[PDB]
Image (cartoon, coloured by chain):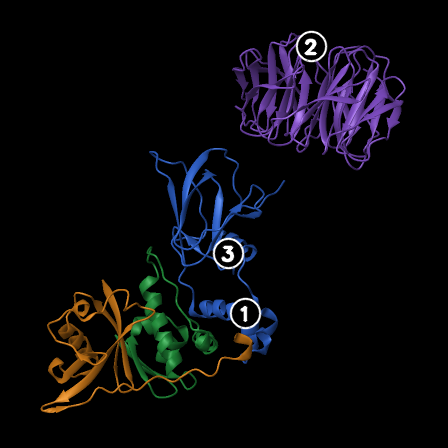
Amino acid sequence: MDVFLMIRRHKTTIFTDAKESSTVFELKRIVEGILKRPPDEQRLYKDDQLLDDGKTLGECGFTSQTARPQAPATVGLAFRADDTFEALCIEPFSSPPELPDVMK
Amino acid sequence: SPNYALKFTLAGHTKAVSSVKFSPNGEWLASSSADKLIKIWGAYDGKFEKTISGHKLGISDVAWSSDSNLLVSASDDKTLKIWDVSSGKCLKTLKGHSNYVFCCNFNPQSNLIVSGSFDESVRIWDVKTGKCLKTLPAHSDPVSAVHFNRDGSLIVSSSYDGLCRIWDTASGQCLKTLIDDDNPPVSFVKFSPNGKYILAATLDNTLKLWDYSKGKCLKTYTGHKNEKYCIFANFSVTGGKWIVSGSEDNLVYIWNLQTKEIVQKLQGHTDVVISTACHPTENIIASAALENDKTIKLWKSDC
Amino acid sequence: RPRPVLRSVNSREPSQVIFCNRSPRVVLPVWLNFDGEPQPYPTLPPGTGRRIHSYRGHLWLFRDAGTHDGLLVNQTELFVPSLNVDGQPIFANITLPVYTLKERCLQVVRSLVKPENYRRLDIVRSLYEDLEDHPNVQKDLERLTQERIA
Amino acid sequence: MYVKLISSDGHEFIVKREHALTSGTIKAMLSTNEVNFREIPSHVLSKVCMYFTYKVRYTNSSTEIPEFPIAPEIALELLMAANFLDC
């Protein structure tokens, strides 16, 4: 069961996929490859729920039908250096203009 | 070679003429039309005798009883009607088909009527009572023609399913099917005067004479156009032995029965000639045409 | 008489087929008759299947019933029934193609904007023309016979 | 095997190179492995990236393919982006 994710921090969004059977630690390894921060310097989140490294993505509630290619689920990422922990902060995307009259 | 020449044109109908038949006694021509009417005409002078009415929709066919006293008509209204020709009176309305009735005929004894329908059935009717005695539904597409053999013991039917079937009248059971190759839709069939053969038309511009018992085809007549309409065909036996048919190119074709040569093409009609009839004793042909013509023509020859 | 290559053959040999709508669209089955003229059949709601009587060598395609978007059947554009083997019907699995983003966006704007209003849209003119080039069977048969030549 | 696509409002989208190469326009722009889009804002480019994921996943699939969903509010800007990107 593949799951499709956006890993999000500040104004960075990584599109990636993994298995429902994948672990949170394996997700951090993906992140490490891209952002060059080891897993121990990374905290992952579903909404405001911190995610445990040993849990599977399915165990966290990332399912094939809540994490679809065309509608991926959001994982929040916040970094950590020693005893300093950065807060989870995800800058929202822009918004579309008012719907034009002819489209209502 | 015959020399049919036009004697009369009959312009009573206001729509396509579907069928013309001569009375067995030679006196009368009946015509049927998409205009819901049957008309009776003098066979020798083309003089209008009467209109017979009552069908609620177009009429596809008419047929005479052996003593020329009765007509049966087959209508888009899903009924047949038995008529007394002298009165114009509907004696019986035959109800039972569930779609257009296309063809009809009495048996020689004239106690029975046979019919075929778009509903893919052949029915046998009691003339006295007007009750359906049997339904024969083996065909798998519309029935185009139905005919009794010379003693009434068999019926032949033709279908768009590409078969002719021979039925035992007494039992209702099918004795034989003629499936020739490709089986284009069959548009007409009847028994030869001698009862041994069947003349069949297919919508591939072909007429065939069949020895039905042996399932072998003796003759083929071509040169005409027949790919859409169910055009009647005849055996002409009063002078030379000919096959007579209409055509979608608006001509009456006449073939030598034996040689299969076209001996004459009758020019005159302005639409498909859907029906032709041969007078029982004289060398007279009636032809009838579709919507752009709406006329009957009477032709006469020395042989 | 010359006829289009894309037409059913009158084989008169029966084939039982399951039309299986594996699409979120209301599906229009389209049978190409013996002249190559398209004939519309009864529609299938999303999530439905019907067992139907067809014939060997007959030719089908499937569209969105409301918009005439083209759909696939067994991963291709055209479906030809063959002879049933061993009492089993032939499945015709009707699915969405993977549309281009552009085509998908055109589908959606077409569904929102009446044709006479396309040109009130604040977009380049080439897109007005794209919006107006509505999918249809006529157009695809052309393409499919053009493709067929290679 | 990852590239970065940056929206007009400065969001950074990191996607597999294969995915980005769904767009022939992006393939030309890469001939660096970072690309900027002066006229595509983040709400539109996020959606484009979802399309690439969807496209690569379900092309050559023989599965049931779901609809790619597009809200009315974004449809016109997504059309323009798709047109520009040729995807």
The label shown at residue C56 is none
Could you tell me the amino acid type at mark 3?
Ala
Per the rendering, the mark at residue C131 is: 1
Relative horizontal placement of residue B152, taking residue B299 as reference (left or right)? left
The shade of chain A is orange
Chain letter for mark 1, please: C
Q: Residue B254's x, y, as percent? A: 76, 20
In this rendered view, identify the residue nearer to me: C45 or C41.
Answer: C45
From this view, report whether residue A84 is shown above or below residue C122.
Answer: below
- Same chain? Circles 2 and 3: no
Q: Give the chain ID for the purple colour.
A: B
- Disc 3 packing (10 Å; few <14; some 14–19; many ≥20): some
Q: Please, what is the three-letter code of the amino acid marked with disc 1?
A: Leu
Q: Could you say which is closer to the camera, residue B42 or residue C91?
A: B42
Q: Could one spot residue D31 in this view of the protein?
A: no
The label number, if any, that marks residue C65 in the structure image: 3
Q: CA distance from mark 2 to mark 3?
A: 57 Å
Mark 1 nearby-residue class (10 Å; few <14, some 14–19, many ≥20): many
In the depicted structure, whether residue B272 falls above or below residue C93? above
Which quadrant would residue B125 be assigned to in this image?
top right
Q: Residue B249 falls in which quadrant of the image?
A: top right
Query: Secondary structure under badge 3?
Result: loop
**For the residues bearing labels 2 and 3, Cβ distance under 8 angstroms:** no
Q: Which color has been applied to chain C in this rendered view?
A: blue
Q: Chain of mark 3?
A: C
